[PDB]
Image (cartoon, rainbow, N blue to C red; front, side, top):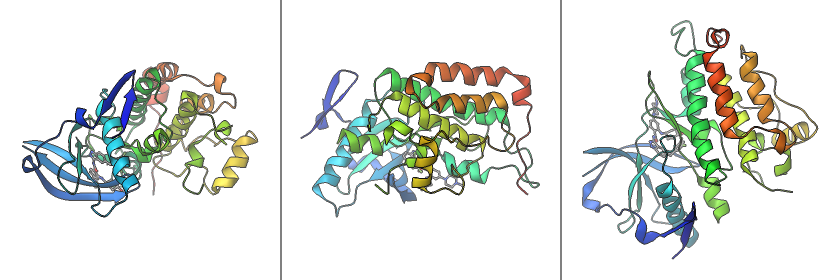
Length: 293
Ligand SMILES: CN1CCN(c2ccc(C(=O)Nc3n[nH]c4ccc(Cc5cc(F)cc(F)c5)cc34)c(N[C@H]3CC[C@H](O)CC3)c2)CC1
């Protein structure tokens, strides 16, 4: 029976909000992936997402699922998905999370690119608001000494597709694994991560790559380079060019997050200030996004 510690506070299985099974109904499948497996559900009525643990699973799998529930249950911030509760005493086991109907950010960006059929589907301001949303979640993690270890568009969710959408950090799998190779998010990692010491400046680095994902509208970073090619490229001083039509001031935020030395990268409070500035600059927000023909 593991304990989990966050912000100086210790908690364990008995501290999770166990929701009676009978109160939980699955509505439909949403999908599966590195994050595990998730459904839309209802509680009691409260609409939720439901993550599930396979009944056929290892002991470490069980401990992983428990630790996921502990980690997410202890965060308290408007840009990190909430945990409504858990159902660990019935099988298959469930973790109940805030329903994020816009789905993951990477897919939303790819699917919502301006096209002749939808030429104003996104504007710079939409992208800067997503960036600000995730920076605010990261600033919370930084201030609570929690290193995320995989800040990327694939790990962010949106409340809804339309106007008023709020982005939130939706996955903590890597952090869970280290709380405790080919799968490592190499394209998101700074040179120093290859002494292997992490800090919140490693998350600053990763946030710069997420900014590149956002302002490229969902491209894979380092187009054409493999993991090892990226590693050698960034270690040598190599950096991505700005995404298509990216305003200079937004690209300058990326390039400061990618300073070789970690002390030279901004903390998330500074990143936020700089995103706020870009957001107020008419020349940035009046810049047209590219049309994908
Ligand atoms: C058109 N498009 C509209 C949005 N729709 C949705 C809506 C909600 C969701 C969805 O799961 N919403 C969630 N609401 N609350 C959640 C909490 C945890 C997770 C797991 C997760 C976290 C994450 F950061 C990224 C993920 F893709 C999946 C997911 C959710 C969804 N999920 C797909 C994402 C694509 C992935 O490959 C398979 C799971 C898709 C997909 C279809």
